[PDB]
Amino acid sequence: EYAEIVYKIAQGFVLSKLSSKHDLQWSKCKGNPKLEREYNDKKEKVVNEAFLAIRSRTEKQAFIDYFVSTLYPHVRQDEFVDFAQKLFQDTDEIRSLTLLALSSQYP
Amino acid sequence: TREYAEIVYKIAQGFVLSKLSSKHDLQWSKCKGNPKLEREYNDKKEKVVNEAFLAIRSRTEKQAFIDYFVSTLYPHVRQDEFVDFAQKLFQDTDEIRSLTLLALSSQYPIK
Amino acid sequence: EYAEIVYKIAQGFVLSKLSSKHDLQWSKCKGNPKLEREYNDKKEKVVNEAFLAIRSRTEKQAFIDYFVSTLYPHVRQDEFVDFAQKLFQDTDEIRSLTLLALSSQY
Amino acid sequence: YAEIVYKIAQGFVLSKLSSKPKLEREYNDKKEKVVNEAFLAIRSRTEKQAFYPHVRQDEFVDFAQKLFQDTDEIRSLTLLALSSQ
Amino acid sequence: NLNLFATILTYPAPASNYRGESEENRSVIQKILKDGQKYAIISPESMRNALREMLIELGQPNNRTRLHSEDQLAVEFKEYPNPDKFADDFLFGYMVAQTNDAKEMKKLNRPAKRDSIFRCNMAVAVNPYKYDTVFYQSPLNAGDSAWKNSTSSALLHREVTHTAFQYPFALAGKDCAAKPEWVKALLQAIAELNGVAGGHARAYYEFAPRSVVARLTPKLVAGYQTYGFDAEGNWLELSRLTATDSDNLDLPANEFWLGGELVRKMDQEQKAQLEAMGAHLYANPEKLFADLADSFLGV
Amino acid sequence: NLNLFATILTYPAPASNYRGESEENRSVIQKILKDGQKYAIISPESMRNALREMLIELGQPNNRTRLHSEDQLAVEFKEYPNPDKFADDFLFGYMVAQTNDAKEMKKLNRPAKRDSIFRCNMAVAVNPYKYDTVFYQSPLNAGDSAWKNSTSSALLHREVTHTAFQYPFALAGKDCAAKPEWVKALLQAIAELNGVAGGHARAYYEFAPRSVVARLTPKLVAGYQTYGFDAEGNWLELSRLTATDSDNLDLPANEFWLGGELVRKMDQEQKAQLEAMGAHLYANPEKLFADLADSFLGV
Amino acid sequence: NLNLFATILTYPAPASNYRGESEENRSVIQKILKDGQKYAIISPESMRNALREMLIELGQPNNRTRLHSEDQLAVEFKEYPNPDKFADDFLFGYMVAQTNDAKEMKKLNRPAKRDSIFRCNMAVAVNPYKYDTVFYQSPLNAGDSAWKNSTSSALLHREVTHTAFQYPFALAGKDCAAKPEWVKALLQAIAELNGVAGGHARAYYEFAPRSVVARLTPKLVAGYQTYGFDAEGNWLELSRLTATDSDNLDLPANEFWLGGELVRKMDQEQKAQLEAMGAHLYANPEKLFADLADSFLGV
DNA sequence: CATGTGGGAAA
RNA sequence: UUUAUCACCGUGUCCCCAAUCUGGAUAUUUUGUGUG
């Protein structure tokens, strides 16, 4: 679904990194407010680190080299082909799309 | 979009308030009883909003306006309609530039 | 209802621009007749140059971008979005109201 | 021709997997995670390391294609293999 | 033999030559073309002013002179503009009338100046505009309070483009009594044009040498040309069919073209064959106006 | 002999002189051309300021001087601008006033003054911009106050290009006998100059003249040069056909040509034939460009 | 007498001074040059801090000192900055101003320090970079679980090159009132400096001795050199022209030729002919500096 | 004449 | 509801301007265990 794929992969990446750093399954946070505070702090730290990392480099080959390597998209078993074939304007636009998606997720 | 127009106004005012709160650790909640605090509060608001307005008005272009808007501005939190609003944005942007100019310029304190 | 707010916008623009440019207000103007004369003639000059500038460039983008000037006077708190949408769509009666409001101040 | 890269990557990964009931599922899940070590070694390459329908034609033609846009090939093995796991 | 059509283009260089106005602190430039792109132009009256200045440069009497005086833009107008003015008034310009005094200025001349022998048209950038700008300056104040200018230190902008543009011109050869003395000055001036800009303190730009394609025909003001070159500047593709059939196949004859700077292109084979028809020999455009002006004129 | 054109080159070096600004901690560099690549520019008014600073350095009396004062950029003017004063850099400027005294100090000179006898143009990096950047960390935090800067430390970015660049300039022989020594001092400053870059302590390089390839002519401020060289500097090929036969075949004359550093190239067989027409036996640019002053100027 | 241009001296050895950060656990080095290869660089500010430390170890009263404290990168600023400071601030530095208190620091000096007497430039590896790398690190884990570090034990990468690099710099004379006592120590520090790298526990690198071809004349900050050696350190690509010259005819006028570690190269006969006019009698760069520092100064 | 909000995916 | 008719003639948007002043990505680390 094009942009929805970018949104999903960004959200999955941030969740996967948060799970690798700290215990997953946020529903266990439950009532203890300090757990919410520390969870939000770690979330925003990871998100703004990625935000800076993608912001400082948005120029053609380096951008994609950092984007594909450090992010884990969905499978897109056969629908990915169209996503790959139009890669030039795809990158030219998904720089802004990825920046917007990353900026969307702050506490 | 009228819904997206409200989104633009809300995100502009939220960016202004949040940047003022973070940069100069100042809260409007302390307004009552400290009129001098009101002067430096309005001075800081003037500075930040004037800088933002001059920066946004400085140049008009597709790529420059789009990437400045997505980089230096932090949009609000919504679940799904961002895809629809963004995709509608990418065909035509001049009206969005005018709307964000209106929202940002409406933030000037009176007198 | 938007006609009144447009008129107030123009009046506030004129007064604020004059006060910012040449640090003059109404009371000290009431002070001595020479200051009425000076402030009045400068107000005529500024409103005349604004009217001359706005009388041309009659289309969507040109009128919108020339509206970007004047710093969007006294737009105030956006309690109403209908001005942002319907009036931007109409883009014709707004020019007439702005011209009439600017001409009304002389 | 991206689908060709996808197919060859998937087929070769399954070939290594076959080379050497929740038990069946976890076995496949853990083994595919193991094979990822080979890919991080391959994606450490910069220009020069590690070099189906037909054999005669590809060497006559695809050999030229490999050497002109090798910069493109870096996304193929990285993007496609990662998409699997 | 009695008409002369030509178009002149320029070398590429960064050119601002601001003309417009705006409070937005960006000195806008003029755009007229509508194909999804913007093209910069130069209005012809600036070129007319440059021509007048160059006629002033050489020995040429004139009645109109620009003075530097009070802030209103003014001209010292000197004598009555008579049609028998050696250089400026006869060649172009008009004699205006509001009251027309008494008995038609003692029954002298004619206040209806209809003919403007130099016919000029605007230029087209033939290169799409780019939204690039330059952050070239900040105004600064005075410290000793002597002749104090604007109070604050402002900031503004400016934009430039790397472009080369062409313009057409034409004139009809009718008179031969007074024109031959003054017309030669015009042709020399056209070869060299200097000015046609807002301020040459920055981005001084000159467009003197490049390929030219003058055409003189007794066709009573008729032109097969289009008044436009390519991005590279090889407009001559349309004449490829025209040159081949000079002798036969019911198409224009061998004396049907003139050359310019573009002849120095690398290829040579068809230049050898094109020599059999046209006068494609002048490598220097300045030399071209020395000869073909003689043929068009009486001598 | 009443006009002078010239273009000069510099040695390759890492780039500097950021102009634009951005919150992203990246000091951007101004760019203009879109031919599929990007180039860097240096605006001419900065070089004009450098020339004013150098004329300050050498012993020439002038009435404009920069002062370090309140954070608003300011420069005092003391005496009123006047044509008849030891000052020539202070001569160029024109500034209006609402009062403007009594007819510009009672008819003494005239306020709106010409640009200058000197005209210049922007520089072009003649090398495509590359996306390389340099990364540095600036700690600003003190443990004992002493009026510290912002509380939190930061990490910043710059960008730099290893290139060399050129720019043209010109002047006219309208008024030169009135300012012989002023033109001599100006030429001495042009022969070698300093600054023109924002970053002194970092990325230091100066615009040492690498080649000068133009002279004077009585052609009334017209040229032929495109104002651009190849990457290696041996541009003369595009003018080789223009210079080899300077004596005949209606070609530009020999007197118009010079040589800077490129003349010292290892091949010398053709130097013998070019010496038969043009005066280009100069290897050091400073001696040649000083010798040019005597020929161009009245003395 | 008032200007000093100098060159650089280094030895080949494995590299250090990483700046980049790759998530793939590699310490990438900085590359800026684009001629088909990569080159290693070191920012001049690193060398500026190294020079500050070298002045610190010698007796020099300063206001800036580095402290190891809370994880924010802090710098101890001591008392209020002084422009007549005995070590650094006069020599090179700045006095900050966020609001600049009241009445210009209670009527004390001038806040902004425009001059940075030490004027240097970025370094260049002058040896093409290779993608050679080595992973010599297998990080560890805690076994007794007392104040544990990161739980996992990962694998990373490092890259180094066999290279020697140079960094041009120059300075001029400003005011001999306090110049000698600080500048003489500064020249000693230049002749012998340490660090300018984070990694010294591994890849210990020093660039103290090598050839120097420094150059000083009162030519008003003019540089004819290119600021670059060849692969094997033979600057002779210019020594054929600007060194063999004997300031007598048709050659550059110079009298301050200097040598370094290159004077002892295999051939010796031409050293005799260069000794007829040059001063390249120094095998030690230290001895050369000890004399040329006194020569450049008043005594 | 002024500030507000969450959560998943595959041979 | 008929019949005929050039909106005509001229015109530099021009004159001055710097994105300026300072800034060590630094801190640690067995590719280790084997074999006709």
Image (tube, coloured by chain):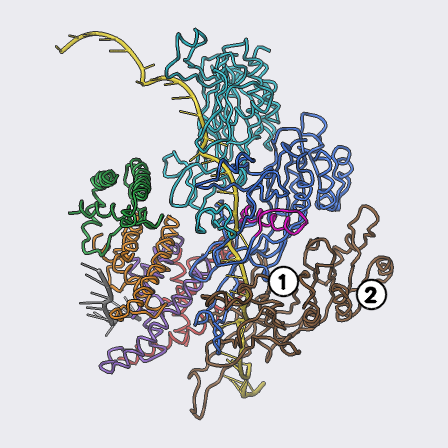
Chain colours: A purple, B orange, C green, D red, E cyan, F blue, G brown, I yellow
- A51 lies above or below F254: below
Quarter residue G7 falls in: bottom right
- E78 lies above or below A34: above
Provide the residue designation for mark 2.
Answer: G281
Q: Secondary structure at mark 1?
A: strand
Q: Is residue E133 visible?
A: yes
In magenta, the rendered stretch is F41-65
Which dot marks residue F103? Answer: none
Few, some or many residues within 10 Å of mark 2 (<14, 14–19, 20+): some
Q: Chain of mark 2?
A: G
Among the two numbered marks 2 and 1 on one chain, the one whose residue lies closer to the N terminus: 1
- Residue at mark 2 to residue at mark 1: CA–CA distance: 27 Å
Q: Amino acid at mark 1?
A: Arg
Q: Is residue A74 visible?
A: no
Residue A82: percent from left, percent from top: 34, 55
* Relative side of E228 to G171, left or right: left
